[PDB]
Structure formats: structure tokens, C-alpha cells
Image 1 (cartoon, rainbow over the protein chains, first blue to last red):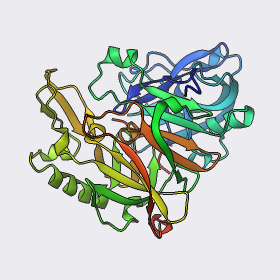
Image 2 (cartoon, rainbow over the protein chains, first blue to last red):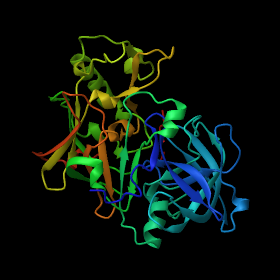
Image 3 (tube, helix red, strand yellow):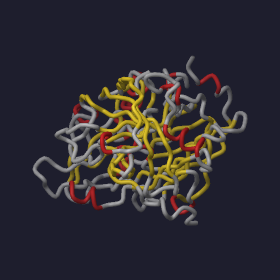
Image 4 (cartoon, each protein chain N blue to C red):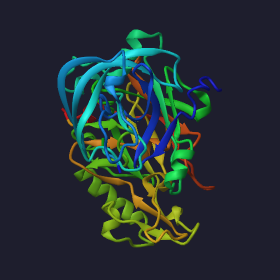
Amino acid sequence: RGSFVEMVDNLRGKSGQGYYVEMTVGSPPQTLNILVDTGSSNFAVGAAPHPFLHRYYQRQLSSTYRDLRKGVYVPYTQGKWEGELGTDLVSIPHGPNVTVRANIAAITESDKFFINGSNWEGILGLAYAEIARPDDSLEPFFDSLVKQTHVPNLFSLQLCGAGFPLNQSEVLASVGGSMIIGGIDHSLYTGSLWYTPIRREWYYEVIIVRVEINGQDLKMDCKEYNYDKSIVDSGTTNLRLPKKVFEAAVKSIKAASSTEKFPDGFWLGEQLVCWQAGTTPWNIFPVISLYLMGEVTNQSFRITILPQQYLRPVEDVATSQDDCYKFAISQSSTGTVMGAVIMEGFYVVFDRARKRIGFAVSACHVHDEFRTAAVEGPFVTLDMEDCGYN
Amino acid sequence: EVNXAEF
């Protein structure tokens, strides 16, 4: 049901630029749009004028600001920033009714971090201390939140991809999803919730034990699927796979859709392809199933996405009436990354309390009249622990 | 696109 109404629909944005929630820092409260990123553990915000920022954190205006006299540097797969550490009172307008003092990195320098038009000025690293900068002694935001309040050690995300391009004004006007803090709202999904164990508390790491393209087993040593790790990251657009897995999957995805030929630039995620209005040939593209280690011994389940998920909508160059997309699956040299496009198909529950991650068909996932995303199980699978890379 | 941490 509508368990947490005050938090439903509190996100905005899209896979390409990121999903963000509204937050306030300081006294008096300073409103800022914060990118929700489960792929990192640092809470940082722009603290100085930037051509891509309409606003930013102003420490000298916060009576509750506290200087920690320490610098911090944080590099991501793509983009990085430098800033000064401190703490302050923080709140989430559309979230639990509480205020907590959290560590905040005031970004003073950055390169390829902020996105023009994204509308967010900071980032919320929801992962664990293990990968926090400068070190694990810097308590991550969610941790501070649980220690200081009675909010359950859990949060769930519902990222809603529109299924078509969204221009600046409409991205700002539309609801991009919900981030339920401290609970699970049943109106955000259908079917049952299946859980996969969080292998280790640093990134939100899971283990993929099998991969299928339209039912066909990619048939690779499952260790490849998790080389050198597999994480869930709302801050990554595409579904990224380690080189060898990417090469096999693309070869299989190309064979399944062979009735049409596409340029290499398309499969490299660099160039888009367009089709006459409403004629995208979805049925020629295969569904992709990722089996994940289950909670019960030798048991697994699978999540299945449609091309409506891995083909990312983008406005045509000549702003035509054509429906154009980009291949939202790309190579990776740092393991698998189940990004926004994968998440847009499901309601993902980060059960930190029970050290597990649950998936369920999203009530807002894009599909057609012939297929829908899915989460099914159980499946008898042996030696899944071995699928994990060491 | 966004590709958010290196460890």
C-alpha cells in the first residue's frame, strides 16, 4: 500500500544525468538538489560558483557549520573533485521528519563532475565507510542518519525512466521516482521481492551466477560475470560489463537482432539510431536476464530487462519526430555495474540491516503489450560462492 | 551519461 506517502515521488532526473533528491544543509536551511549515488560513500556539495550550478552551499552563512580543517579528494569512474571537510545539520524535506549532523565535503575544485542541465549541485554517497575518502573514519551520511535517529537501517529506490526523451523544462517538471528512506512502499512494485546477499559491505556488491540473452545461456565461467566485482549503482547510467563479458553479450545481442544491422558506433554506445515515430522494433531485441545468488543455499533468482531498459532514449540531433536511442550497455575494466537503466526496471531495496538487496518489478518500468520486465525464481544453482572473484 | 567511486 502507500506505506510512505511523504517520500513517494521525491526524485527527479534521468539515467543519463542522474536522479536527485531535495536536501537542506545548514541553519538557516539551504536547499540543494543532491544526486543519489549508491556507488560511493561521500556526501559532498558544490561550495563555490560554478558555470553548471545555479546554487551552492555557503558555509559562512550557516550558524551550525563546523570546520574539520581537513582536505579531501574523491575520484570516480568518470569525474572527480577536491574539497574541504566539515559537518552541519542536514534534512530531507520529502523524507523522514528528522535533522542530523553529518559530514559534508564542500567541493572547491572539480573536473567533469557536475553536469550542465542536470539540476543537481551535490552528491549523496549511500555506500559504506570502507570506500569513503579520505578514509573509513569519515562516517557516511546514512550511517549518521541511523545512529542519530530511529529510522530503520534500510532504504529503497524506484528510478523511473520516461521511455522517451525529456527536455530541460519537463525533466524539472516530471517526477523521476521515489527514494523511500527507512522502509519499503508496496505501491512502487508488483509481484514478489527477491533478495540477493550483499557479499561485502563497501560498495553494494552482489554476485551474478548466470546470464541469458533471450533464454540463451551466455555460458561463461560465472567468475567472469563478477570480475573483479559486481555492484548496484544508481549513479551509473549504463549496465557496464567486464570486457570479456561485454564482448560475448554484444555478440549474442547482435545475433538475436540480426534482422537489422547497426553501425559499430551504436554498439559502442557512442552513436544513436533512430526510427520513424512509434516504430521502434522492440520485438527484434532480446530480453536480458541476470541471475543473482539467492538467500537460500543453492538457490537463485533472476531479473529480466527489456530493450526498453537497455536502449536509452535521446533526442535526435535534428530534433525530429523520430524516436532515437543509444545502446546503454558498455565495457568496464572495474567489474560489473548495474546502473540506472537496469534499476529503472525494478524497485530495489537496500536492506543494510539484513545485509541483502532485494529486487521487484517496478510499477513504473517501461514496456510494451507483449513483454514486461521480470523477477522470478527460485532456481537450483550450485557453487554460487565460487562465482565471486577473489 | 554519468559514471559516478574508485577504490
